[PDB]
Image 1: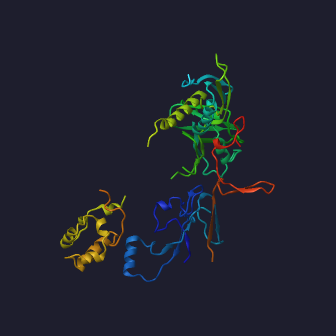
Image 2: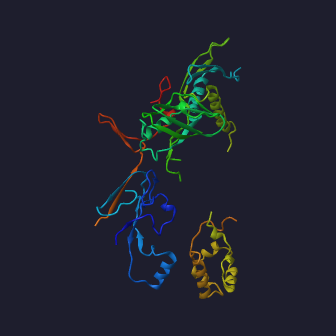
Image 3: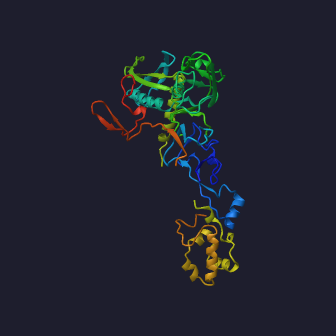
Length: 100
Length: 305
Length: 50
């Protein structure tokens, strides 16, 4: 399945998602340091077999957690600065998000 | 007499301009003019207090590497201009000023909203220019008192608050001269003239008095010359839910704290009487329940208590 | 095989510090060794430092 750029990452806290907009992209003018998230992305990992433990995990913590994994873009360690510009390139035929 | 020095006094102050002054001290003994002058120059250039701009909020801007429509200057240039704003605060160590302007023309320091305890010494200081008739600017400026130089990098904030490097020192330059003093009946006395250049936010006489007070306070030391362990380790052993026989065995070995227990190795516990392998396994299990182990080494135990 | 690309730009400011390299126009290069406080510098009769 296709990778998705989104602001809904299941395995990260609310504080770490505070500088991302509704599209999963950092705001203009944000002060960032090493380890901060710039673009939030997930990669599919779904399987067609559901074990009882997997069913319990999906029932208690939701189905989104069991389907995707974090592959976000993070600031390299030892790098800091201010976000001054963001550009989005989309293949012709794919729907555009709010930021674009 | 030999052990009788003449004490200098402040004679006159010449206010050449609003930011340029001369202070005269008289009389001075042989050699004291330079001794006082150099120390006073160093203290005046180093340790005088003043107020400076530290933070700016502009309604429409998000960071400093940007532009505002209808404004001639960049945000960085506006911040640099605000870095050179001279303000005198009369009653507190922090204040927030407000600036609102619209229409074509220069925006200067005379457009800042009046405050009771805030004085602008150079109302003609240019802040920016508006080049469009349907253009307006509004900002909030934070001013606080300090001394020295504090860069903004050494000292979360919402997006839109811009930090400014702080130069608190109001003194621009100091010069001094030692001349002959025409005293009544002696010709071996000197006179010290100090030329002071500031930004107009501090009085020369109080600057001299403050420098002298700092020097005397530093001298008073020469005038009288003379010559954490982790909390869990501090808990008692009975905090562990050990069995009755294990507790008796540990008490027989005079072990009363976790720090005492974790320093003992497995071999020593095994060799102790009345302690089998089962009880040692239970002790290891209860220690592992808290992320601890046997065989740890500690320096300076007991922890001085 | 590429769906989308996002590019982010970060701006930082570098100040002068010991270890930075300075030069003139005549081949006189050097490295900064010390930042000296204002009252330690040599000055002239008017009190102006270098």
